[PDB]
Image (cartoon, coloured by chain):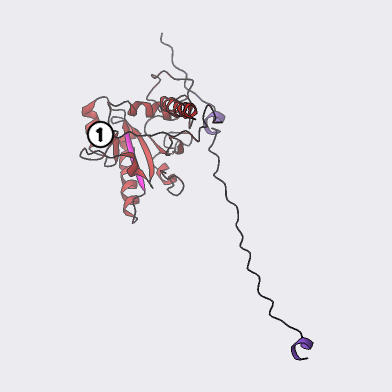
Amino acid sequence: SQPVFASPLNVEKRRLNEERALMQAQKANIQLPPNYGDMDLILFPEGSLKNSNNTVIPQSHLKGKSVALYFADGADPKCASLLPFLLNYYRTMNEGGANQKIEIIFVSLDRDREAFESHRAHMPWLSIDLENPLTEILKRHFRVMKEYEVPTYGYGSRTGVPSVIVIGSDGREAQFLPICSGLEEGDRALLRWDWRNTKFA
Amino acid sequence: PPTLPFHGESAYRTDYVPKPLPEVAKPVEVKLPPTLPFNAQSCYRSEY
C-alpha cells in the first residue's frame, strides 16, 4: 500500500498476493491477510515497455538502475519547457559513467496516437503506449491528474503534469522530484535525483 | 452555474505520509583470537 492504498494497481496486488496466500493455506499457521512487505507484484508485464524504433523490452532489464516515471503531456508548456532539460540530464548522466544508471519510462496525456507519436519521437528512453490500461492505472496509482475528471477516492492532487517519480520495484514511490509540487522549483529538481539509494531491485 | 471541484490537501497529509521502515538486521560479529600455547617453564625444574 505504497504510496497509497486505494489504487487499482494495489488492488490488483492485494488480490493476487492474498489469493496466493489462500491457495498456499489450502495446500498446507500462515497469516491472513498477508503483510504488505510480503506482497510481491510484477509492475510491468511483458508487452508494456517499448524502447525506440518499437522493439519489446521487459522489466527484468531495469535491474540495477534508478528508474523514474515521466508523466507528461505534449501540448503542455511546462512539458515543452521541461523535456530538453530531462534530455540533457539523461545524456550527461548516462555518458558520465562506465555503467548506465538512470532510466526514464514515459506515460502520456496526449489526446491521440498522432500526438503520442509526435511527442514520442523526441524521447529516447523507455515508453508505455497509450491504449493499454497500464498508462492509466499508473496515474491512478501515483495521484497525477490533468484536472478533476477521474473518480477520485478522497485524493488530493499530488502533482499536475509534468512529473517525474523515482519508483521502486514493488511500486513504492522512492522519491518525488518537485517540479510542480510543494517546492515548486522547476527544471532544477532533476539535481535532487539521487542514484545511490533508489535502485530498481 | 457549474460547481468547481475541491482540490486540496493539507501539509500534514501531503508530506507526513507513512514512510518505509529503514532496513536493519546487522549484528557485529567478533572473532576471538585463538589462545597461544603456554611454552614457559621453571628454573628449578629446568636445570635441577
| Residue at 77%, 88% in the rendered image | B43
Q: Colour of chain A?
A: red
Residue that badge 1 annotates: A119
**Residue farthest along the top direction in this orientation:** B1
Asked whether, in this view, residue A68 is left or right of residue B41, the answer is: left
Q: Position of residue A156 (x, y in %)?
A: 47, 25
Query: Does the magenta portion include A177?
Result: no
| Amino acid under disc 1 | His
Q: Which quadrant would residue A128 be assigned to in this image?
A: top left
| Residue at 63%, 64% in the rendered image | B32
Q: Which residues are magenta?
A: A97-106
Nearest the viewer among B24 and A38 is A38
Q: Position of residue A166 (x, y in %)?
A: 41, 39
Asked whether, in this view, residue A157 is left or right of residue A115, the answer is: right
| Chain painted purple | B
Nearest the viewer among A168 and A86 is A168
Q: Position of residue A107 (x, y in %)?
A: 32, 32
Q: Which quadrant would residue A123 be assigned to in this image?
A: top left
Asked whether, in this view, residue B22 is left or right of residue A80, the answer is: right
Asked whether, in this view, residue A171 is left or right of residue A135, the answer is: right
